[PDB]
Image 1 (tube, each protein chain N blue to C red):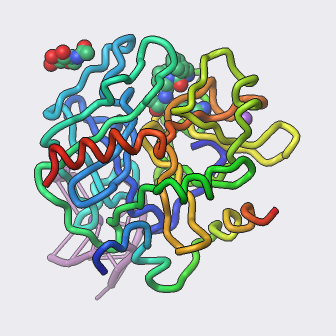
Image 2 (image 1 turned 90 degrees about the vertical axis):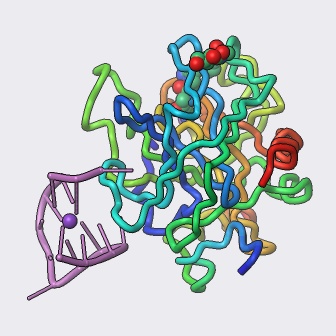
Length: 30
Length: 259
DNA sequence: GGTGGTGTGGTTGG
Ligand SMILES: *[C@@H]1O[C@H](CO)[C@@H](O)[C@H](O)[C@H]1NC(C)=O
Ligand SMILES: [K+]
Ligand code: NA
């Protein structure tokens, strides 16, 4: 923790995914 | 936000509520980009046709929120404004070109689980992510639909809303409206064909349009909710200030007037 | 209530 911009304490920092972030990642493929 | 859903707790820790002191009301969204700087839409601060011209003292900023109306004791933090900076070429007369403003807080805010800044994209990141068909995410406490009864309590969410929307090709944006679109804007939303729906709406301005990099796992703010015609209409799209195209002005303001 | 509607709280005290 220093320039940890854009990494959420309750999500990325806990290796938890939010309920819809899957949808965004799929949009880079299809 | 139209056709979105309730945010999870800590899902947009960079979300900021811009709040009018008197009378006491929600004005707009905004985003936290460091410990002392908040980004929003210029029209939230200055829009003469609606008699809007706020200074530092009219406004509070509220950070860490989930509920729209309740003061979230021990969660949310409230900061006062040192200074507002509106883009010098902001065009309120025609088409809200360069709909962007920076707000310096009097004191840095202490980060928490509920409060944490978003990244701004560099050139590579912009080019990689700002492509038609890729989805981003928009968040806000604005209206749940285009409102036709002048004022309602059924138009407003109790908690922060979220929706994911695809970015749209510049020709489709350009044909969907007669307002003159610029390279300081992009549009997003589903086509009438795609069957899915959703949009930002009035009250969501200043809120961020963010994308998650599949390379470093970080969230970047690519846009600012700026304008539209109605909300969630078929064949219309939401318009967003293009953050990367204005990044030189952002850097310049933060370097010069910056602690 | 206090910068909602119910808690041996909650995203948080009493
Ligand atoms: C906005 O309002 C303030 C009134 O305090 C005024 O001094 C300022 O010049 C206004 N700006 C514009 C562009 O109307
Ligand atoms: K309580
Ligand atoms: Na639409």
